[PDB]
Image (cartoon, rainbow, N blue to C red; front, side, top):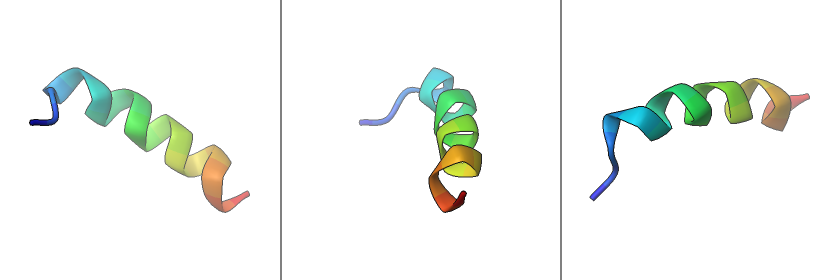
Length: 19
């Protein structure tokens, strides 16, 4: 239920998420 497109954003959000 999670499109591959969000993976990109997810990864970017992640970087900003932990810091």
